[PDB]
Image (tube, rainbow over all chains, first blue to last red):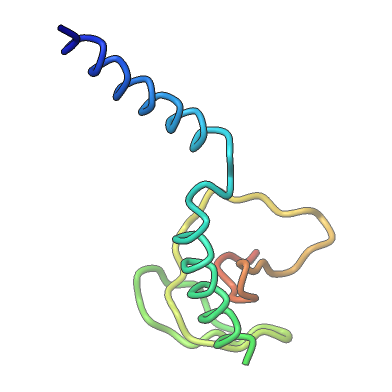
Length: 48
Length: 49
């Protein structure tokens, strides 16, 4: 009945995610802070 | 003082800057009243002759 509708649902959710990432800076936060808590891990290491 | 060399690991002994590295030509621009540049982690990555 609705292969097209379910596909549109999945891709529309995908597009909402795309808008969230292109807008929300904290959307990937859990890598970002991990990158950051790695970054000033090294940065503290050089500040040290 | 000594002349400048490129693509060779040499010591750096400036007025107040010490280190060892490789000096290559670059495209950055500095303000008239500046001496040396830094990166985010207070590590030099470009200087004026």
